[PDB]
Length: 384
Ligand SMILES: CC(C)CCC[C@@H](C)[C@H]1CC[C@H]2[C@@H]3CC=C4C[C@@H](O)CC[C@]4(C)[C@H]3CC[C@]12C
Ligand SMILES: CC(C)CCC[C@@H](C)[C@H]1CC[C@H]2[C@@H]3CC=C4C[C@@H](O)CC[C@]4(C)[C@H]3CC[C@]12C
Ligand SMILES: CC(C)CCC[C@@H](C)[C@H]1CC[C@H]2[C@@H]3CC=C4C[C@@H](O)CC[C@]4(C)[C@H]3CC[C@]12C
Ligand SMILES: CCn1c(=O)c2c(nc(/C=C/c3ccc(O)c(OC)c3)n2C)n(CC)c1=O
Ligand SMILES: CCCCCCCC/C=C/CCCCCCCC(=O)O
Ligand SMILES: CCCCCCCC/C=C/CCCCCCCC(=O)O
Ligand SMILES: CCCCCCCC/C=C/CCCCCCCC(=O)O
Ligand SMILES: CCCCCCCC/C=C\CCCCCCCC(=O)O
Ligand SMILES: CCCCCCCC/C=C\CCCCCCCC(=O)O
Ligand SMILES: CCCCCCCC/C=C\CCCCCCCC(=O)O
Ligand SMILES: CCCCCCCC/C=C\CCCCCCCC(=O)O
Ligand code: NA
Image (cartoon, rainbow, N blue to C red):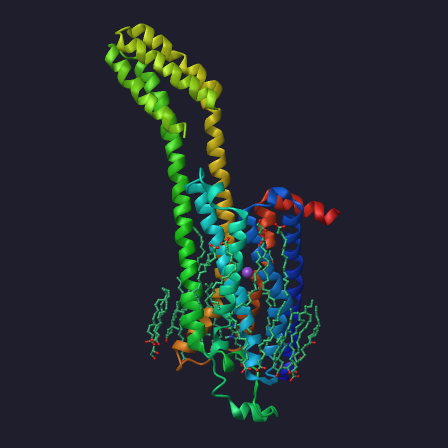
């Protein structure tokens, strides 16, 4: 069958993906530009991610369409159109890893996040990561390429000129570069690092949820212990456990000032052997607990849960990157590691290529379904 028929389907699908990648990610960038509630360090990496995806639509997809034709080209110019998508994929990987680390810093050390993670430092990191992405993605242009060994029969068959090759991805980009350097070192290792970071994020959240519930349970149990206490020493033991626990949750302010002060009141009576007076003073903690501590409780729990939700949203983005890019990388592994295996058929290569490009469509939908500030800003933009 004429190659232009299957090529037409592949090209049409690529162009449809390009249109969607541009539109959705321009909308992401416009939302962040317009909404100050979306202007934080996390979303600067989101914007860097959306910029890479815009460039997939504007440049990498036109480059991929071009390189599927095998047109005659100078080999190094062919290398650049082959490899520019690797720059954009690498930049996405750095942004995804930055977002994960950012969310880890926010949940592990929230008291120093604002002083540690600033807009100026984030912009500097983004710039450095773009430079590194060009270095990593265009490494074949530094000499790790197949231009020294052109396929002359294919070039002659296409009527190519002297110094030109039929411009095809696997003819110019070495597969050991793609498998060992690009896939294993530059993609697989950072994704596994991201997985580790997300594991620590969710473990940290669960531990802090446990601690909040243990501190809450300790407060209510020791009050009950005091009520059924007999000597002053038992009242003293329970209040001491409450006081240390009260200060531990103290790391709203008036409520803990009342709580500690009321614990100290009962402790002073307990040390004087006045059990009934200490027990009666301790019953007032219940008034403080209802009016302050429980509210100062579900708010921290609510905040942690919002952080879990935001961490899950970021993790879905990273996971969709892995799902969309892994088939093409896995095919490369088969090409490289199994020379006795027939090459993956051309329709599957096209499917794996277009799947990798669909990843540049999906992030705006994840933000729309999972982040209210984005969803609400999207709606206002579309209406206006
Ligand atoms: C900022 C944006 C708009 C710049 C876009 C520039 C792009 C389209 C340019 C820059 C370098 C160019 C390549 C440089 C060299 C060659 C080799 C030649 O034998 C065929 C064309 C080819 C393969 C060019 C294709 C077009 C190209 C990729
Ligand atoms: C969802 C993601 C993470 C995994 C997807 C796995 C895909 C990419 C795997 C599963 C089965 C695989 C195929 C199994 C057998 C062959 C025949 C061989 O001659 C060429 C490779 C080829 C054609 C493989 C290509 C890659 C393949 C299609
Ligand atoms: C997703 C993370 C955890 C792992 C990535 C999966 C990669 C590294 C694995 C999954 C399946 C593997 C392939 C399974 C089968 C074969 C055929 C054999 O003749 C050569 C190796 C080769 C081609 C393997 C190479 C590595 C491979 C592609
Ligand atoms: C992630 C980087 N990357 C790749 O690894 C890749 C690729 N394209 C191919 C193979 C194409 C092909 C193979 C055999 C053919 O006969 C053919 O005919 C046109 C085409 N690979 C391996 N691109 C898309 C340009 C790509 O972005
Ligand atoms: C903002 C615009 C960005 C670039 C627009 C689209 C880019 C298209 C990329 C160029 C591939 C086509 C050039 C190769 C064909 C001519 C070479 C030949 O005929 O031998
Ligand atoms: C081919 C290059 C390979 C080595 C790349 C070295 C990294 C390039 C660094 C320059 C980036 C310029 C921006 C520096 C400002 C960062 C300050 C900050 O972190 O806030
Ligand atoms: C992360 C998920 C990874 C999924 C890996 C899927 C690959 C498993 C299937 C491997 C079977 C490949 C064997 C095909 C040999 C071809 C025989 C031949 O053509 O001579
Ligand atoms: C030559 C290619 C250069 C153009 C790349 C195209 C993609 C860039 C997209 C725009 C970056 C968004 C900048 C402002 C968005 C939010 C950032 C902010 O205001 O804090
Ligand atoms: C905002 C602009 C974004 C890009 C617009 C341009 C769209 C270009 C579409 C595909 C370019 C394919 C070029 C065809 C390669 C030449 C084929 C050949 O010479 O044999
Ligand atoms: C937005 C500013 C961008 C600045 C220009 C970036 C493009 C660089 C242009 C030339 C270097 C391209 C490398 C491939 C062309 C030479 C290879 C060859 O012909 O054999
Ligand atoms: C192919 C990969 C090559 C990598 C080479 C290593 C170079 C990268 C080095 C790290 C960049 C850090 C930039 C810090 C300097 C300016 C920041 C500052 O003002 O404090
Ligand atoms: Na991306």
